[PDB]
Amino acid sequence: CHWEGNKLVC
């Protein structure tokens, strides 16, 4: 999981 701009992507 990574943090993109304003949210969590997994």
Image: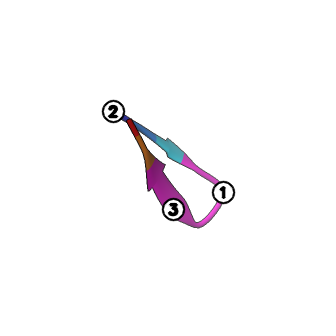
Q: Along the line of sight, which residue is nearer the eye, 5 or 9? A: 9
Alpha-carbon span between mark 3 and mark 2: 10 Å
**Residue flagged by tag 3: what amino acid is it?**
Lys
- Structural distance between the alpha carbons of marks 3 and 1: 6 Å
Measuring 38% from the left and 35% from the top, which residue is drawn there? 10
SS at circle 1: loop
Name the image quarter holding residue 1: top left
Direction right: furthest residue: 5
Q: Give residue 7's mark.
A: 3
Dot 2, crowdedness within 10 Å: few (<14), some or many (≥20)? Answer: few
> What kind of secondary structure does the magenta stretch mostly adopt?
strand
- SS at badge 3: strand
The answer for how far apart the CA atoms under marks 2 and 1 are is: 13 Å
In the rendered view, tell whether residue 10 sits above or below residue 7.
above
Q: Which residues make up the magenta segment?
A: 4-8
Asked if disc 3 and disc 1 are in contact, CB closer than 8 Å, the reply is yes
Q: How far across and how far down the image is residue 2, in percent?
A: 42, 35
The residue at which mark 2 appears reads as 1
